[PDB]
Length: 47
Length: 253
Length: 109
Length: 108
Picture 1 (cartoon, each protein chain N blue to C red):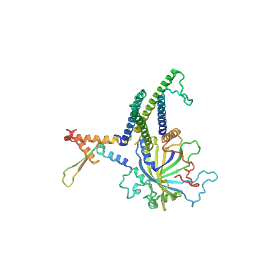
Picture 2 (picture 1 turned 90 degrees about the horizontal axis):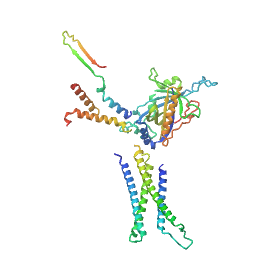
Picture 3 (picture 1 turned 90 degrees about the vertical axis):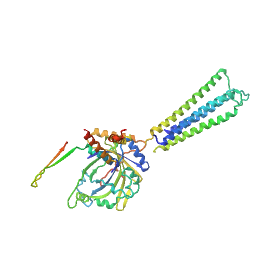
Picture 4 (picture 1 turned 120 degrees about the vertical axis):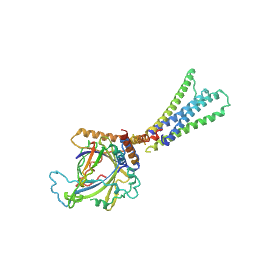
């Protein structure tokens, strides 16, 4: 509604990529026969 | 339920801009736009409430207020999207006409609120009023609608109006409001606060028994009033004007 | 307030005019006047007290002129001080900027 | 810098006290000339009228202009804020510095 609150919200949201918690994901696909391919997904977080 | 301690006043639109600047010089905050829509409901006269204890006057019938916020997309006409959404738009709101008409409000049909006449006695420096409040979050059923709900309780619609203005937040929980009021009917829309702004400064107290807090609140309100001496005169309104019981009809506007 | 300053400057100006006329007449007829007619009113009875009254006039006009001028100057400065004091009056680019900064630090750390 | 209106206001005020100083100076010369006029040389008699007239006209219009200024005070009524944006501008400049840090070709 008011300009000031939206301006502050925009400026604060601009820093999300720095302030937010880092995350990582690693997907490992192992080559197996008999159309049986297990998957190994490891996600690393720092809560 | 709160004890609201309030002071009132009015100003002509000519000084409006100037007034705004002075407020920002004191509070250190910028104004924030807001709007609202209030509907007043009264007990149904078709039903005879013999339960009013006439020989004892345990209670008297009263009026219920239902309030809701309405987005500005209903209040801005085709000539006004160019300007940004800030307080200056109020400078164009001097005509008795307004984009929101009767049909849209009828299509709409929240916060439920009841109040009492202020405390008696002539040794009161600020208007002290008691308010009982609740909130309606949602509903369901075959007739889920505000009108059907209030008819289920036993109340019927009386009138409605629209407030548009600005808000200032100061220290100690003090809130200062500049308002413009538009009454709405099928016949049309009429601005009761014609050529001016209604000013209201108030604080809320959660518990009426605490008296140290009430004394502090009164001290803050009187200090604020004594700060604005010479520019605007803030006064205690008439105790008989803020009475909203059905038996006697008048409306401070 | 300002109206009081207006009035004060008013007696300031009229006092200047009156004391100016007084010192003018005193110095012009400082040469004592002797006229046989009863209409004239100029008396010099005690010889040296005449000079005392003369230096009286001198000291009065000096003090009053200096005080009035100084008061006017102080008034002007006060007005100027009141004038000075009382008159109350992209985001995306930042996103890639911070992204490059953080990746550069991560590589360099 | 201050808005221009204040600038010509202060210029007018400065003109006011300079005119007052000129009035005092002319009072000094008229007091000087009256002495020799009382002495008895009539050569500087014509200058006396001019000095008196200029002294009075300097005394009058200065007060008139000051009256105009005080009148301007009457209608000029009604005609930390920087902090509200101060952090913002600080923010801006800091990121600018980062840009200068981020580009090694501009650090020369």
